[PDB]
Image: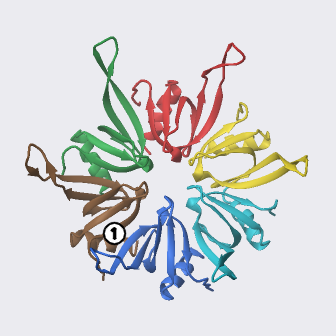
Chain colours: A red, B green, C brown, D blue, E cyan, F yellow
Amino acid sequence: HSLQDPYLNTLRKERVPVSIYLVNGIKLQGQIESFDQFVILLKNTAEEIQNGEVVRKVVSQMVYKHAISTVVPSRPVRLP
Amino acid sequence: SLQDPYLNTLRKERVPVSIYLVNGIKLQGQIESFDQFVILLKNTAEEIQNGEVVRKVVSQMVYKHAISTVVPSRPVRLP
Amino acid sequence: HSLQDPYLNTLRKERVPVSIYLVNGIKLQGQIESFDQFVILLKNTAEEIQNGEVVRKVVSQMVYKHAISTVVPSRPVRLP
Amino acid sequence: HSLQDPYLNTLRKERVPVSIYLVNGIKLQGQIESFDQFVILLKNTAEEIQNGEVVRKVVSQMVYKHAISTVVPSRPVRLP
Amino acid sequence: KGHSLQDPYLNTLRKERVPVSIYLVNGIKLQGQIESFDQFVILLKNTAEEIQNGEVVRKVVSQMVYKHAISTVVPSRPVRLP
Amino acid sequence: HSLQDPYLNTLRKERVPVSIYLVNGIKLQGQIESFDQFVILLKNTAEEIQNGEVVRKVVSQMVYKHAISTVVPSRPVRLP
């Protein structure tokens, strides 16, 4: 895959906020900290309300490429 | 051997394609570039902000394995 | 592909109208123009009304084998 | 296919009526005419009615293994 | 740690006639004992019980499941491998 | 596998409680006992009511990776 590697690699190093849409329709958000041939490591640091104050929770989840339908970043970018 | 050309045709000829996903989602745009396992689809979305229409370029990396069918706008013959 | 490549070559060369059922339910109709190891190119003249006249549209769609469940030809076929 | 081939090759030989359940919940009944590495030619000997006349078709649909969840034969069978 | 786990787990599930639940991705639950498996299918035997003319009838049911349609396989009792 | 095996292996070594989301929507909780190229052996210790007292039931599923949506660890995990 001579395009997928650059593209992710780009999105990761430039810390590009992305939406990962899953085949089951679930939308993940956040940044590609890392990836390999079969998985993306995706960190999202969304805000949260814990007992009437604003906490920010950083859950990082490994998402299987084979369950991703599309990867639509927040801003377009190009490869080396 | 059929896939690459059909794609590579649509890419260079930059014909707008409708690519239906397995879940039924219909994505439209132009094939900027494709890979063994992914298609980079380019589209210019239209948004309404403060009355007037504003547009920008959205680029989607689409996994081939979530795609069912690809319907181009106009039929195309291979090279 | 002892059974597949013939059963499509026979379907392709003999221009048999085929139903393609997709895993997701939606049914495609039309003739196999051409296929490779992962895709089928299915061409189909349709029947459309625009401005009170039956107009026919020839639509060609590359359909990923991996979204296909079953392909049912219009008339029984044989191979060598 | 130490197990899959023998088993499939059995049910074609002994012309064993099989139900094939697809991943999407579809159930096909029929006899395994042929199969290869990725596909199964399922012959269905199905009666039906057309406008108050019994009409018996014989349809040979090619099924992609990747759409099959389970194949359930009508009689228990075994192989070497 | 490549393909060491799948066989041993299955292979001791089969060899020790352990009852297993097989959950298909589509949400179907299949119960039975693993008779055998290759790289791509497991052969699941169970005994089905129907009623014919108001008397019990046991039948042996043996179905070939594709692993690519299996989500998870949960034995009825803990097992361990070599 | 330069990210997946490491990420998995430290989830396993540090007995991190993990939630495994399936493509079909099912959430599986537990911890990675072992994992393969294609399966995760996931152990779950849950409390179950037996005869008016509470008893922990240990359950161990072999999960197929290809049915896994996403792997959400209980807490952050940094690899070597």
Q: Quadrant of residue C63?
A: bottom left
Secondary structure under tag 1 reads strand
Q: Is residue B4 above or below residue A31?
A: below
Residue F34 in percent (x, y) is at 75, 52
Q: Residue at image x 78%, y 68%?
A: E18
Q: Position of residue C3 (x, y in %)?
A: 39, 75
Viewed as shown, does residue A54 lie left or right of E8? left
* Image quarter hosting the N terminus of chain C: bottom left
Q: Which residue is mark 1?
A: C72
Q: Is residue D54 above or below residue D28?
A: below
Q: Is residue F75 left or right of residue D70?
A: right
Q: Is residue B37 left or right of residue E64?
A: left
Report the label total.
1
Chain letter of disc 1?
C
Of E63 and C40, the residue lying toward us: E63
The reply to whether residue B78 is in sight is: no
Residue C69 shows in the view: yes
- The residue lying toward the viewer, choosing from B51 and C10, is B51
In the rendered image, residue C29, in percent from the top left (x then y), is placed at: 27, 60
Report the residue at 55% width, 78% height from top.
D73
Q: Amino acid at mark 1?
A: Val
Image quadrant of residue C23? bottom left
Image point 18% across, 45% down: which residue?
B74
